[PDB]
């Protein structure tokens, strides 16, 4: 696609987060409500990733979230952040991004 | 900052890359030229990260790059991609982002 100014990257609020609550409705299927600790507040996202990852696997996991996306409703649940993943070219597998070493919840993602 | 449409995230070309060449000019200081394999092509960036990371440490490392930023010159060297990092709130330490598991060079970064 076309370039991209630095300003276009800057308008995004991306932070390291840690998953603190993973919720599965009883009547099921596909979606899970996830709470992500982003340092001084906790933001809700609706995922997506669970059979691929376990619920137990997601708990305490360090992740990367986009935090200033327009409020979204999915099946009536609010998504106010979204997890960043790398996905294979055929959509078969999606893997969460993470800082390569341990880092505090809430630290900003920046270009080097 | 203000929200953020999905479209604003979509205009960015972010991919998983692998560092394949790290170059240090003899007359020194701060900057290093890094080649990043992004699957079917290799893109140049100018970093930044080297004393913090070794050159040997960077070689073969899986990273995340923004690939469609306006061509930039730094000290006359072209930067045509930029590495994504998480940085502490005081700028003291910057850590490269990575998929949490091994993934091929070139796979796209997407929101879940």
Image (tube, coloured by chain):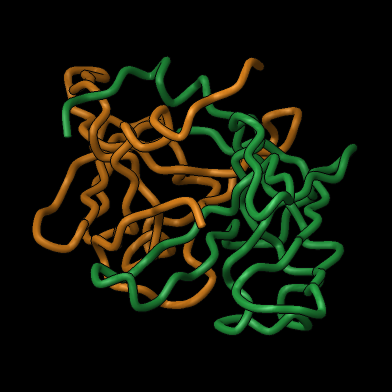
Chain colours: A green, B orange
Q: Residue B55 appears in which quarter of the rendering?
A: bottom left
In percent of width and height, residue B28 lies at 32, 32
If the image is split into quadrants, where does the N terminus of chain A sit?
top left
Compared with A29, B7 (above or below) is above
Q: Nearer the viewer, residue A77 or A10?
A: A77
Residue under the point 22% across and 61% down: B20
Direction from residue A97 to residue A104 in the image, left or right: right
- Residue A82 position within the rendered picture, expressed as x and y whole percent measured from the top left: 60, 48
Give the residue furthest to the left. Answer: B40
Q: Position of residue B57 (x, y in %)?
A: 43, 63
How many labels sit on residues?
0
Q: Is residue A112 visible?
A: no
Q: Is residue B81 above or below residue B42?
A: above
Query: Residue B32's quadrant in the figure?
Result: top left
**Residue B108 is at least partly visible in this image:** yes
Residue drawn at point x = 33 percent, y = 40 percent: B66
Query: On the image, which quarter does residue A6 sit in?
Result: top left
Q: Examine the rendered structure and indicate whether residue A70 appears above or below residue B109.
A: above
**Point 60% across, 74% down: residue:** A30
For this view, does A37 lie left or right of residue A92? right
**Where's residue A53, x and y in %?**
61, 81
């Amino acid at each position: 696609m076309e370039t991209v100014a630095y300003a276009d990257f800057a308008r995004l609020e991306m932070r390291v987060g840690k998953i603190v609550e993973v919720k599965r409705h009883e009547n099921a299927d596909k979606l899970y409500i996830v709470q992500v600790d982003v340092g001084q507040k906790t933001l809700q996202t609706v995922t997506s990733l669970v059979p691929y990852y376990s619920e137990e696997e997601l708990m305490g996991k360090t992740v990367v979230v986009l935090c200033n996306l327009q409020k979204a409703k999915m099946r009536g649940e609010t998504s106010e952040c979204m997890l960043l993943c790398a996905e294979t070219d055929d959509g078969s597998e999606s893997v969460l991004l993470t800082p390569e070493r341990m880092m505090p919840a809430g630290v900003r993602v920046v270009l080097d």
